[PDB]
Amino acid sequence: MQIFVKTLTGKTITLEVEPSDTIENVKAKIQDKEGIPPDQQRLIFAGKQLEDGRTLSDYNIQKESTLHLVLRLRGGMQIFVKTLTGKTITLEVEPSDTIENVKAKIQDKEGIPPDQQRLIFAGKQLEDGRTLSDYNIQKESTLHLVLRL
Amino acid sequence: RLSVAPEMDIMDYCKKEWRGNTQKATCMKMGYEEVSQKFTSIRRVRGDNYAALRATLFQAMSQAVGLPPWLQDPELMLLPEKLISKYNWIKQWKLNEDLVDKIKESLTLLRKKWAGLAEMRTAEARQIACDELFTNEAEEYSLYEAVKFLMLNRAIELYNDKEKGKEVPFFSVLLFARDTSNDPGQLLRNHLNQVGHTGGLEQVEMFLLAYAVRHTIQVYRLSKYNTEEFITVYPTDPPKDWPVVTLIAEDDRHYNIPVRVCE
């Protein structure tokens, strides 16, 4: 069967599923199609927020049913990355963004390869896989970028 | 210093901010170009967690030719006492005195400034004056507090309206379906209080902002470039007499201001 998942803009996504599919399976499928991370994903049906462990048949979701996708992504925050040459880069970020993502964005903006990037905050070297909030990096905090070879 | 930066050419800004060859940078460029078709300039908005409110409110007030009826209604000035007396739990909020005087002060400041800008000889004078308004962190944050309060009130109205079975915009249903946002109280505690401090506004909450200041918020989302979501509107089906303000969000993590008619 096929089901519909709608965003807040009315955009409709079509998913190929079985009623035995778990909700996290659906989230993973949505990741595979639209590129949206599951942790940012929140699936809602009949005014209820669906749970990762449960399946579709558990919620009595029939074929051609419509699920709504409400993202956990906030937005409204930026931070600064200061290069050793003096220039400051202003990044638009979310507290749940990984260091991997920050480095990737730095590559997207300045062309600097992530593998060469070392981000330092408060004397500590930040590690890929953790988040800005994990390091208590607030809005308008400043990070220091050093490069290697 | 202004929380809304002086304007610079939009593609010059794009070239400055996105270099390097990655599909992301390309997408950003294509989006920025598409925006550059209808807007000449861009103004960087400060990235403190108030950014959504800052952009929407600046845009709304800088073009305001008249005081909106809802802002003019004197009953509004009685809203904090009326609302807080009814629902005690509202007494949890953030930045001798009390919450009622603070919210009333803020609402008064909002109405006063909006009305002041509205009655001025020339549009130019209004634009410059609004620029003068977003310099000082104090009056600005007072305004944002007022806006947050309006968002809360409108939210409460939607929840109450649903509970008695009245017709409501669907975003309200989706809003309260969140485990953290189940009731207006939880909305205040887990979401609104962090707005301006530890976090920004979720997309669902942008609807609430739009309904709060009664302005249609048009957003260019550059990450959405070749899709039908490239231009996203809050709310989806807006009242016809509401003014329209325009924002830009690259990756959905922040909002800046596109500009056409400037000083």
Image (cartoon, rainbow, N blue to C red):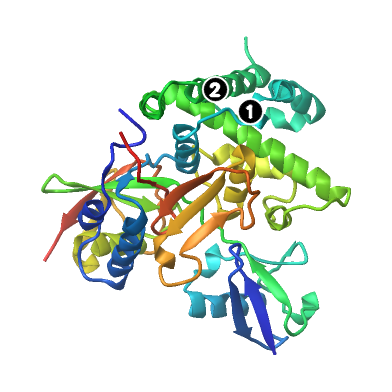
| Amino acid at circle 1 | Leu
Residue A88 x/y as whole percent: 21, 46
Q: Which quadrant of the figure contains the N terminus of chain A? A: bottom right
Mark 1 secondary-structure assignment: helix
For the residue pair A68 and A20, the one nearer the viewer reads as A68
Point 46% across, 48% down: residue: B246
Residue A100, located in which quarter of the rendered image?
Answer: bottom left
Chain bearing tag 1 is B
Q: Which residue is mark 1?
A: B71
Mark 2 → mark 1, Cα distance in angstroms: 9 Å
Point 33% across, 41% down: residue: A141
Residue B256 x/y as whole percent: 39, 46
Q: Which residue is mark 2?
A: B115
Q: Which quadrant of the figure contains the C terminus of chain A? A: bottom left
Residue A148, located in which quarter of the rendered image?
Answer: bottom left
For the residue pair A127 and B65, the one nearer the viewer reads as B65
Using the rendered image of the protein, determine whether residue A133 is visible from the camera's viewpoint: no
Which residue lies most toward the right here?
A: B164
Mark 1 and mark 2 in contact (Cβ < 8 Å)? yes
